Length: 88
Image 1 (tube, helix red, strand yellow):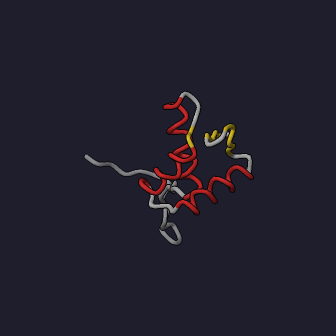
Image 2 (cartoon, one colour; image 1 turned 30 degrees about the vertical axis):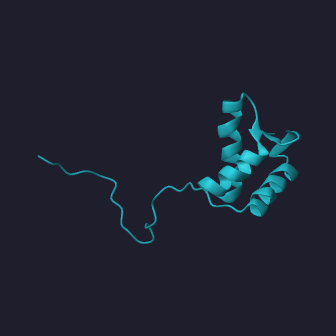
């Protein structure tokens, strides 16, 4: 019916046995850059990133601009034109 099997174990610390993957403000900004790049044929207009981050994720313009500087500074992204962001 069922049968027996081998390689017995026991449960001491063996909780928490699940995967993890999440998001962050840095991630959520960067996600908009790539999800607009393909749409613009390689642009992410910085003003739209701001407006859409306040829409999609309630992030205030000051904070979106800070995300923009941080990831720019890291060379994770760039601003190749006067209000167009790019992933590195």
